[PDB]
Image 1 (cartoon, each protein chain N blue to C red):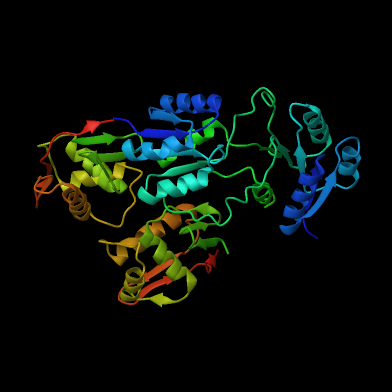
Image 2: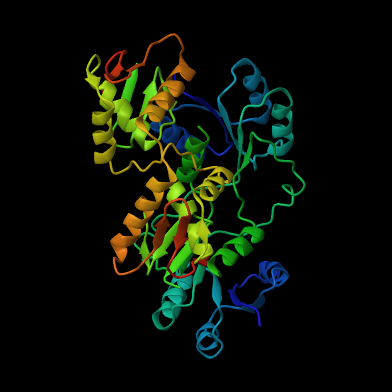
Length: 218
Length: 216
């Protein structure tokens, strides 16, 4: 159960070469000698991608290309020139000032084929963004760290000193404000989206507590 | 004073074509057709970049490039590309499932070549620069720099500079005015020292003490 690729190529040597490269890339290559055979094959045995050699000038490639596109939206890679290997490049050491423009290699053909074939509170710490009921929140890095801290352990009272230590451990957080300022600001932005939800409770000298749902981390 | 680029191409049409495209990009192109000519040219008249076609007769470009790389670290682009296929495909509608496999065009290499190659404020792309050198400024530092330097000698209180940071929607920080000013001055003094940029007086405000900003 791997992606199958139909190679429409007349030249037998290159045809086999593309088969060798594609099969080695864990694909299922199939070769066709152009002509009438192509169309019914695409209808009965549809591939996941069509590698088509437009024998330019010819125009017979483009005509077949246009014919296939009429009844199917299967991706077609229109080969313009003659695909050749460059084994001279293999083993070549690339420095910091050595820029090698990509060749017209069967390797690069395989490469392009690979490219073509590819809790109301949600917090993503990979991109550092949060959302309440789907609505995005515009938070400063401190308001974010406090949001994730409280919402991860809901019903847990965090003292003002504890939250500071979560802000200290989080570089990308530099703050001249106080904890009370942030909590109000974060709550203000949360109440902007809801106003019907009890988000953060503040008991002086005791600490802050998240009184909403547990954040879902992505 | 523009970047000099050496083109090593044996094919005359593509050679002249690369010259035209590169010169149009405000560069200084020089074409060499033979492999025995380039090496002494790289010595006597060193270019800023070498556009080297991998496939030229007489001597292969790889033994040619290994030679240049031995006595210079000038950036070398290894070209394996040809002319572009216009007219044949001109007018064709390229769908989301239509992928064109074609060799690099002389337009594309010039594109790739380009990639390899006192106070001014461009409020468009939101950047600044002092004495040529660009400034890495946070949205608050930028807004503060423009506000202060637009009117040198004028005193803004911290209450007023807060009004500006509040009216700027690019600005979202956890820092105060005093920190941004300390920062903005720290980055300016990192460039050229002994030049007094911002003066801060408590209870009075802040004052830009240098030349005015040149906008856009």
